[PDB]
Amino acid sequence: VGFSEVVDTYWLNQYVLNREAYDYNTIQMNYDTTALLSAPAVQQDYYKLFDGSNARDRVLGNKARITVRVRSIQPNGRGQATVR
Amino acid sequence: VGFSEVVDTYWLNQYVLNREAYDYNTIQMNYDTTALLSAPAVQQDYYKLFDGSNARDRVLGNKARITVRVRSIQPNGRGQATVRFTTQQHNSNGTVEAPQHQIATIGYTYIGAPMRSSDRLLNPLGFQVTSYRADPEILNN
Amino acid sequence: IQMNYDTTALLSAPAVQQDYYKLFDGSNARDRVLGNKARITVRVRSIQPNGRGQATVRFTTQQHNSNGTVEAPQHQIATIGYTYIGAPMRSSDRLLNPLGFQVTSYRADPEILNN
Amino acid sequence: FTTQQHNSNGTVEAPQHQIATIGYTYIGAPMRSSDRLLNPLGFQVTSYRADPEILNN
């Protein structure tokens, strides 16, 4: 049975925007996307932002939302870039 | 060891194109259509784009126009999809501005068939945007 | 027009598509007569189905132009024979006609306003 | 044809415009006094529909 700069700046932008932004209505995709674009260490740091009494899910919840936009990204080396 | 979307993308396209686009000559239909395909919260956000001194109606007016086209839409969950599209500005002097790339995130549902002839002939399915945002795409290619 | 043109073809049986394409051919082509000097605005007032793939469309039309003038509006009635061919299998078609609407017969005559 | 609604509070609704399509025949004179004094010709509708008129004027 069983036998049968352009590219990096895009990812850096989408990562920051989705990571930092928040909307009760779309966050499940941004949340999973951020994790998909994060090393387990990073994923955990991110997941923790939605934990405890100060969780983004409780602080913003469905009462407030965060809008994020990237102005400029410039790579600076060997796996490293700055996002403004 | 050896053992080892069609309908929603249409509405999302038509919504973004009509919402983001502008032409003095056709905007009344795109404007009403956008509202018809929007939750009151969303409708208000949209209506406000035509208000004040920076209103699309005053900035573009009948001097400049916006052309919008959608490249690709991919649903990602439970009332949510990503729309990848472009936009450009044309004007009365015959010039064209460089095209921009944008990505919209749309939260949506359907409210069923409407009960007015002026609505059913535009949105029979009941498509409704409940949340909307669109950011510039950064072409880090 | 490029989108309306392709959309019309997308919603038309080959026989109908050809009838439509021909309106843009020859010296009397819409592309030469209207070109970029004049434009046509169309709005539908009412549609009522009457049978088995057939409906009546009551609509109006008017011509606008580059000199800022407008011709008196005309009234027309279309008779449309139609079916559906199901969902298309190309992204360029499904994002325009997912239902498969297709006109199999088409005519539109002037309305005589005997009011 | 046209149609309008009036009511007990003395108000009147805006008139609407409609168009009927009538399929018909005649069945000849009826054989009852209560019918011949109303439809002696035998008029009979065999199919009927009426849709709103769209005043695209």
Image: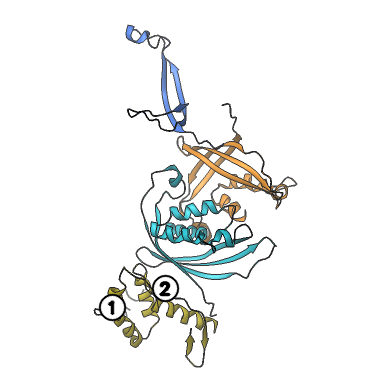
Chain colours: A yellow, B cyan, C orange, D blue
Q: In this view, does A59 lie above or below B95?
A: below
Q: Position of residue B81 (x, y in %)?
A: 41, 65
Disc 2 + disc 1, Cβ < 8 Å: no
- The three-letter amino acid code for the residue at tag 1 is Ala
Q: Which of B54 and C94 is in front in this view?
A: B54
Left or right side of C74 for D10: left
Q: Is residue C16 above or below residue B66?
A: above
> Which mark identifies residue C24?
none
> Which mark identifies residue A55?
1
User: Looking at the image, can residue C89 be seen?
Assistant: no
Disc 2 residue crowd, few under 14, some 14–19, many 20+, Cα 10 Å: few
Which residue appears at 51% of the width and 47% of the height? C102
Q: Which of D15 and A11 is in front in this view?
A: D15
Q: Nearer the viewer, residue D42 or A41?
A: A41
Mark 1 falls within which chain? A
Question: What residue is pinned by disc 2?
Answer: A67
- Of marks 2 and 1, which one's residue comes earlier in the chain? 1
User: Looking at the image, can residue A2 be seen?
Assistant: yes
Mark 2 falls within which chain? A
Which residue appears at 55% of the width and 46% of the height? C13
- The three-letter amino acid code for the residue at tag 2 is Thr
> Dot 2: what SS?
loop
Q: Where is residue C105 in the image (x, y as percent from the top left)?
A: 56, 40
Which residue appears at 52% of the width and 77% of the height? B138
How many discs appear?
2
Q: Where is residue B78 in the image (x, y as percent from the top left)?
A: 34, 64
- The answer for how far apart the CA atoms under marks 2 and 1 are is 17 Å
> Dot 1: what SS?
loop
Left or right side of C28 for B68: left
Q: Where is residue D2 in the image (x, y as percent from the top left)?
A: 46, 27
Quarter of the image for the N terminus of chain A: give it: bottom left
